[PDB]
Amino acid sequence: QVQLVQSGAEVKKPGASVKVSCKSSGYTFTNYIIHWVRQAPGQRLEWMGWINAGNGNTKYSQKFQGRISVTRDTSASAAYMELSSLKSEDTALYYCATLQMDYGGNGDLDYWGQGTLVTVSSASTKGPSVFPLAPSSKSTSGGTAALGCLVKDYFPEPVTVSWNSGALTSGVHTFPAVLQSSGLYSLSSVVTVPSSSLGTQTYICNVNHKPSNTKVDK
Amino acid sequence: YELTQPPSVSVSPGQTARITCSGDALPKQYVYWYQQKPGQAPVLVIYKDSERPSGIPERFSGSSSGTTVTLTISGVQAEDDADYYCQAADSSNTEYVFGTGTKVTVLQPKANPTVTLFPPSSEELQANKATLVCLISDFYPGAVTVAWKADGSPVKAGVETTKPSKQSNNKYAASSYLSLTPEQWKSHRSYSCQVTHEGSTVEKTVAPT
Image (cartoon, rainbow over all chains, first blue to last red; front, side):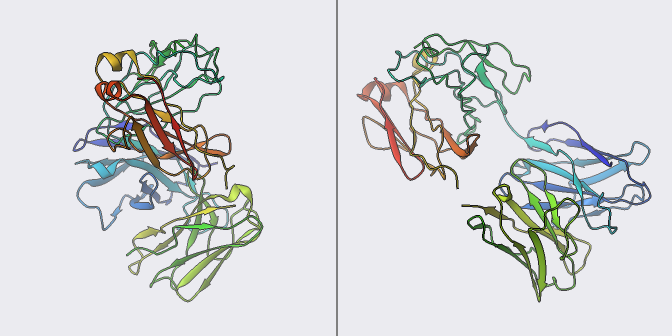
């Protein structure tokens, strides 16, 4: 079948340069226009534009000009688009569109890649999780988490397998400038709260889960 | 030029769901109806205004009348909760546009009252004079984004920061909002009786100063 592949997540400060690649294979390379669209979180899909797989001539959306520039390499079988002067509203997902439906006719964007997510964020973390007494109920009010963590996609959780089950991931509320990724992982057990494993904090700076100390200590 | 469409619908399972996409230059163009599950790329459900691609169940159908195209679902299923879009082109036909998007839902997560659990003050936060308690709701159906931290006083806007209602894995929605308050205010307060409101209910958790 036709395989469509996007690049990984890219994060740059506003006003910087962003480059993202879209590679396609498995279709007759004569003429299959590849569409690029942008999706804001919880918003409508906005059509960025389209590119030719082999032809070369390109059309750009009437709303976005100048910063948009997509040039593909036919030999490389991939499409590259460069956007300059990043804005705050540009934080979004990018999607590619092509054709596989077997009843003919273009204008039918069949497949979509995994998309590429672009945001702006700093890096931060926290240390100790909690130092309260053991609650009477069989639950952990305080768990391994990072407070005021500006790191995007932070994963604060206990290093060991213990306390991972029964834990609801906390949303990264970003009311201030810092992303404040809470990453709450409640042990949800009275016994587990008194003796909780240290909670690692990977943060945006280090993708891998770097070890960190965060225990309920109930 | 942007196509207009209702933003969300709510129809109980077993009843037909109707979505309308309208545009002035619509009768001369074909619409494509796109289905998008949350956290997933959109997928065609209707093309050429009348028929569906392979592998799409018969429950979906599309019709066109005047300047309005209608997607109709007969016997809406549980998995049909998603976002639906209409794709078309403007008068010049060289610009591709998508619809507003209708968030189709069936009737409804398991109703549950708000659960508030104030996290204990961190040792570093206490040392940094920024000891605070954060309340996270385990699960709530249609949780309201209302947080009222009341530490020895009325609700303070700066004490608690509102957060979006995330989707819980257990067929519900989990809301977790981090509340930041100074340690001096917490020390002055007799108890940090932070209250989190979700699911048309309010629960308050009080911790020692």
